[PDB]
Length: 330
Image (cartoon, rainbow, N blue to C red):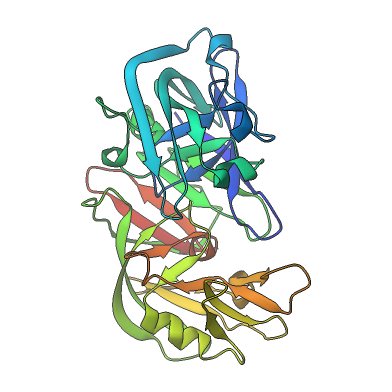
């Protein structure tokens, strides 16, 4: 079996991508944020505190004939940005682009932080990292990808994110028309529960490629590219007027400047991120200072290849017994 779903940016800056997901019987369609940096499928629901809901579509388990309360199970998660959510657990049928899993753990939110409430376009998250990160207790639950694995033609999913445009998430097959050249595969370490890999280096604009190992995670749920201070300083040094601002919380640059591209290595292959993808627009409405898409990972403790990097490539997440990541130009 296979699945194929269109993912759409929530705004003009590609801050996040939402994909329609069918939950329950009859289907209730929610727009979820596919997150390869987490392992919980959680949604806004009829149980979420009324004041913490602002425009989201809610999942209503009482209207679903296949919904079953997972007696005693609770969940609590905290994200890298400081946001959080918690609640109880239901099992129900979940479908993504025609691919169906019965008995998927659907985590119903009772409480959500202000960050989620303010994003009216996101109805929840669908975690695609390894099941070891799932927060359901006392019985840890499996991700949608893990549950679908046996039924898939190939144990893979692909991320093909668009730049200011819709993209595609495919499950169980590799679309050979979605990329150019070959796919370069690289080793994944599952030790921390993430799709963790090692980039072979970088180049700024038309500069010389610097071979240096950069350990990081392929994270669809993070908007920006977070890299070591040394790399990030070398990139922003090529932009006239760029500086790190403590008031803003990162590198900013004059909106009038042109941004060089950024190249990252995948084995012997190179993925080029165009300069335009690194522009996140004015820090405030009418401001002439713009926010950079390449930021330091020093305060985070882990390097993150977020949407800025992933949208420049066709990405294969191979969930075989020996997991790998594939990158191709597109």
